[PDB]
Length: 114
Image (tube, rainbow, N blue to C red; front, side, top):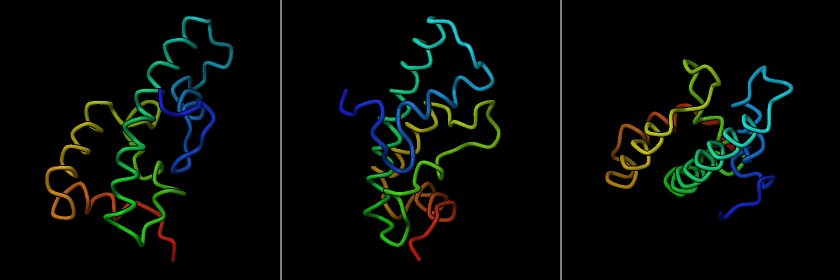
């Protein structure tokens, strides 16, 4: 796995995503810790790929500092985006770059440098 669990990219880390996945489960079993860690690693790796892509497509956006917040979903239980949806977003950016709906949606969401 390419990232230590405490390395922060775009304002998130594996550990911070795991904490969000755990939600109100303040005393999780070892089983729930394992499950949330595996899911958090998968989400983080994908988020980083999207954030790095957007950082170049959108230099005015503070992608490396705050990009993870632009990938939240207000309609999910944890606020994390669905894994398959993140894959769809990355495919859209890889296929169509700044001509994609994903590019424009993310440009509108993200905090700017200025």
